Length: 141
Length: 141
Image (cartoon, rainbow over all chains, first blue to last red; front, top):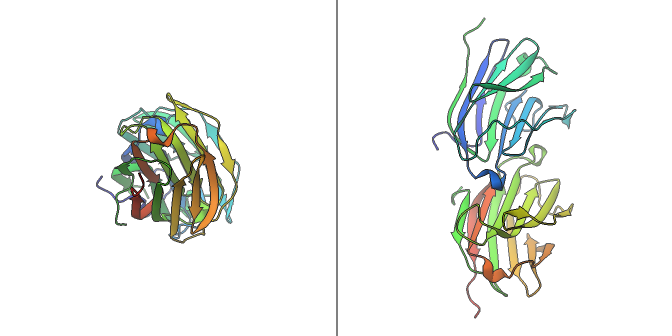
């Protein structure tokens, strides 16, 4: 749709920041489209990932970090609030201890900080979605 | 790039048909972009899949069929002729007994027919690639 995918935006995060994403899967859930959101430490796509969030729509979600080039301990969830064929609204809030992921207004996943969120310099949203909205909030000190 | 992705084309296949695909991954291999090619029995994306070919670039390839809505026996290969950051040329030939997948001119995967190739009505190419060329040959009786 409107925004380019893969979508990359320079970003800074700290406690109180919110990343808001509105989009739609490009395929029915039977075909297992993916969504991935990565919070990177540099603008380069091969840079480390403080927070990796990968949805296989209809199946599972995996979360991880990639540190000095290596994936660390995977967290896997079978929670699946996303609805087949529907637009979704994803909110990722930076809390003192964790990221909190809201899906269509419902708390759905959390991930404890492994690296300070201040290390983030870039957010990438990619895989099998169209994107109509992306925002990072910058209202807090 | 040039062609829309996801890419869908109505198609017919029989012995001697060749499907030729030229494209490039949208991400470095460290980020595990995917490529998927599905030969469908109807134009609808939820239709059965006579031949499913899914590359996780740098990692593995899985092949399967989806019959009456259900995935059948997965075949997994660790053969990985695709090169990080490079354009690829994929050829899929319909042989009497199997599909043969050539990558950059090199025989790389085969998959025995589970359903007659004459059941195919559509080909879809999707996931994390750009596409510059897609062709189905129609020269044989």
